[PDB]
Amino acid sequence: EEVTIKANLIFANGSTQTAEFKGTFEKATSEAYAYADTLKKDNGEWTADVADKGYTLNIKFAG
Image (tube, rainbow, N blue to C red; front, top):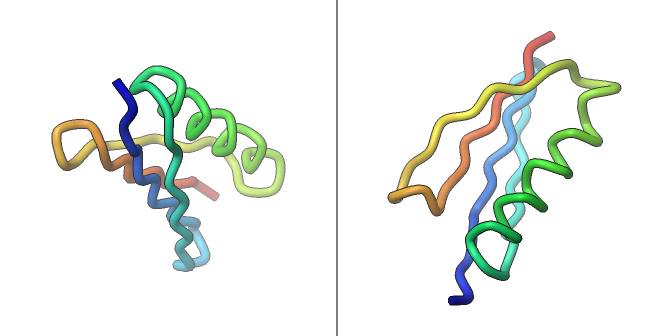
């Protein structure tokens, strides 16, 4: 039931950052979205794609 969701955050500036969240699929994934959401103020809206069968989230922030 416990899994790891790896979130790779990519900003318009070309920089990147990675964070892993551990818990159930829903909880861990939700925490990744929440973190991305806190970064929207200074980084804009984000879109995302999934790799590794949904266990890797590649999140990209617009301008």
